[PDB]
Image (cartoon, coloured by chain):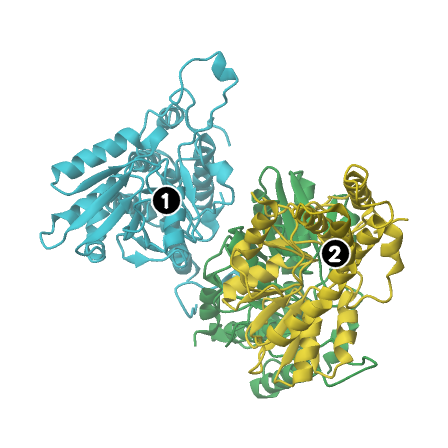
Chain colours: A green, B yellow, C cyan
Amino acid sequence: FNITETYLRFLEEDTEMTMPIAAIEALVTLLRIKTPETAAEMINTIKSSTEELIKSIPNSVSLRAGCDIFMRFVLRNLHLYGDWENCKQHLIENGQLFVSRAKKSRNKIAEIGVDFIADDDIILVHGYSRAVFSLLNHAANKFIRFRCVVTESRPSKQGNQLYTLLEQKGIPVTLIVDSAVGAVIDKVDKVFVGAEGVAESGGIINLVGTYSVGVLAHNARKPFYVVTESHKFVRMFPLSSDDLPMAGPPLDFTRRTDDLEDALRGPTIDYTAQEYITALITDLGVLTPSAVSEELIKMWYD
Amino acid sequence: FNITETYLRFLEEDTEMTMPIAAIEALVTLLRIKTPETAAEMINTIKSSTEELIKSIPNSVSLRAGCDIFMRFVLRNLHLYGDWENCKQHLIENGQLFVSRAKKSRNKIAEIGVDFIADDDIILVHGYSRAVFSLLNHAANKFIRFRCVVTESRPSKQGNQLYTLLEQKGIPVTLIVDSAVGAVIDKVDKVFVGAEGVAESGGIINLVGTYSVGVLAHNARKPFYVVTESHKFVRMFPLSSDDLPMAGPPLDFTRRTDDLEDALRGPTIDYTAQEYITALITDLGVLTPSAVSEELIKMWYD
Amino acid sequence: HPNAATSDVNVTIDTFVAKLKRRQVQGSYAIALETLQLLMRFISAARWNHVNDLIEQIRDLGNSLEKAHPTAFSCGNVIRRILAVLRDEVEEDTMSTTVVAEPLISSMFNLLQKPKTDYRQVAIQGIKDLIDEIKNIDEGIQQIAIDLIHDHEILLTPTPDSKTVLKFLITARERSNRTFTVLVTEGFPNNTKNAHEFAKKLAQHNIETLVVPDSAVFALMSRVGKVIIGTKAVFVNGGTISSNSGVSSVCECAREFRTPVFAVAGLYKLSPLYPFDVEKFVEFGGSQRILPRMDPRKRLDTVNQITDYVPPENIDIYITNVGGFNPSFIYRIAWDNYKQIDVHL
């Protein structure tokens, strides 16, 4: 009963919702039509829907991660081996319940995460993730000595947007180009990066440039930070230094031109290794080193 | 008579006139009017003019280097203890002669120092220098397996200009953002760079982002190269990682604005350390390790 | 929660506080023992009727203790362990009272999905078990510890303040087939006397001892084989608090030279709380010990600290009584000893 349309429906919304959360909700809604009782009629349909979504996907792995998590949850659900109605009801409940959860997670974050701020520490923020922004705003709320540094990101002018968002807060800020980020090593005390997908080992999928930043941090011995909630978990491991399922160009040397038509071709999404990250920020208590892998193991058991 | 006016006179032409050579020519022209026989009336005035030029500078470094070189040359000239007329005449001759020399130097560079790219070595070029471009074009002329990778330069969209220049030569090119530069070091063999000036310590005075690139190169052990015409040796010492005599602001934290006005004030000039250089290509022989410093010593006799 | 409820039932809390504040109690082990004793006293004397309420009370007490002294991690840890022990039993009981499937020992989805007995004796037993664990750590290390050091290898020892590390060294030195040269860094404002004592002990043991000043670490680094830390407290991500002075720089040096960095402590020192700030947990020493006079010393503001914090990037090995572990793995060990809700009190 459609899912692509639902996905499309969320573009100018957000800020209050959460794309992957929305997707999950949509999935749940789809599920509560074709009966969760008959497993043959339902699971296959769900799979088909997921395939369709993948086909319609441009540059996103997080939705897939969400859907597989949902599937896993569903599978777990039927372990009670009792009546087939209560379980169904629970499943039905668990969609808006997921939406509700996000708020609670945020709340949890905003009380433990505020302990990290030290006296006169300058913070650089990279990537458009809602969680990081929330953390920042709720740190301002707490009233702690802090500074904000903006990086000039170029997918569809994201850095500028981030800067603008920061402005409507009242915090003094300065914009730095992604090429010029290397020179800033002593002034910025902590390097903060948001994530779009957390892998097996603890590797991060995000945006236009993260790996380089990580490398720089390693070189300067400055702490590297990953800020996320709890829905972006993929059972994946990259083969090379940077490899992802992409709809865009993986390094394309364009043919001989004069009038300029196609030139903007290359890497858009980047992967960073486990060694670079020193601290991980999540709502599930406090966990850092290799907890994601453990979580995955718990989930899949395979 | 003015030097500033002369400098202004060249705008749309360039692309072979080595700006410093033009400056030297202008200086010579200024000199050969008010009798170069007297040292009291002349050298002081020249110095004053140079000071004025420095004061008037918008965003240029090499002028000073040129002027000091000229001064040194002048000093060298009057060591023959012969006569005032002939020496003066020789000095006068040596302005246009110097300009003439530059072309020969360029030719020497383009015929001898082009052997680095031969067996389909993929080049990562950043920082616009005429010499590097000449080397490229004259390599195409010679016919050799070669491939180009372009990193996006953003002072006032110079990357686009570079791309256009490349186009009028016939060769497939691709654009890479200096954020995803850490992701792509695998297929690209060697890194080549055009510099604004070479420091007393050995390091390179360049553009919007080079230090990070250097760091990346160091990490990857893929060699870092600098190709410049041998007259960019200024008496300047960048003692710390984030210090240079710059006309622009060095990381200015702007106040809390609302209309998004003050943002684009990111570091447009960056410095890298002495150890990063593997080979420095100059017309005065293939010399790198501590050659610039030696030259400086020879000049100042100290 | 104030001390209005506990006045005639339990009095020793005040004494414990006093011990903490003026530093009458010394050595983390002793603190842990004291904590255990306190817990025992609480258990034997007080009344409960309800279980959840009791748990809450315990949590409150723990919080109060933390508020009284933050640098006493062992105290906290022991309490947490006890809580964990209680919790499992409580969970078991609930299942019988009411009258479940799990892929592993603990599940993540169980938090999302909606979920009188003789537990006192079990609780009592837990304390005893903890005490036993505290008693012997070195016996569970030496079977792994005396396998790493080889003939004609040179050791470098920062922090000789810890009692376990010395013992570990001694056990290695016992073996007739094994021979090694020992370089000892002093640590001026906090570790000097202790270092001297350690050196003396080494001499007594009949081993080649080299007393090295804090400046002469760089010259001998071409010969250095291994690095051992005398740490006091272990944490979640891998980072450790060391037993006072001269650890960080040495570790950095080791990292630079790619020298292996070992750590010996124990799981009772291991904490389920994160060290988010260095400034919050690390306590500073005394200015009086460094330089005499007072009136010119108003101008001369001297900086000196007790404890030292080392990042998890430098340290690679954490051998305990159970076995050899990593900073990327030790979190799980903590979880196996302290439960999920017991982290925040």
The residue labelled by disc 1 is: C250
Camera-side residue of B48 and A135? B48
Reply above or below: B137 against A191: below
Residue C4 lies left or right of residue A147; in this view the side is left
Task: Calculate the distance from the C-alpha at mark 2 to the C-alpha at mark 1.
Answer: 41 Å
Q: Position of residue A94 (x, y in %)?
A: 62, 68
- The three-letter amino acid code for the residue at tag 2 is Leu
SS of the residue at dot 2?
helix
Identify the residue shown where x is 65% and y is 41%.
A146
Secondary element at tag 1 = helix
Position of residue B172 measured from the top left corner of the image (x, y, whole percent): 70, 82
Label 1 crowding class (10 Å Cα cut-off): few <14, some 14-19, many 20+? Answer: some
Image quadrant assignment for residue C324 = bottom left
Frontmost of labels 2 and 1 is 1
Q: Position of residue C101 (x, y in %)?
A: 43, 69
- Amino acid at the residue labelled 1: Val
Q: Are marks 2 and 1 on the same chain?
A: no
Q: Which mark is residue B205?
A: none
Drawn side of residue B241 relative to residue A17, left or right: left
Q: Nearer the viewer, residue A297 or B32?
A: B32
What residue is at 21 percent from the left and 55 percent from the top?
C149
- Residue A162 disc label: 2
Q: In the displayed image of the protein, which residue is found farthest to the front?
A: B82
Quarter-of-image position of residue A232: bottom right
Given the image, what chain letter belongs to the residue carrying mark 2?
A
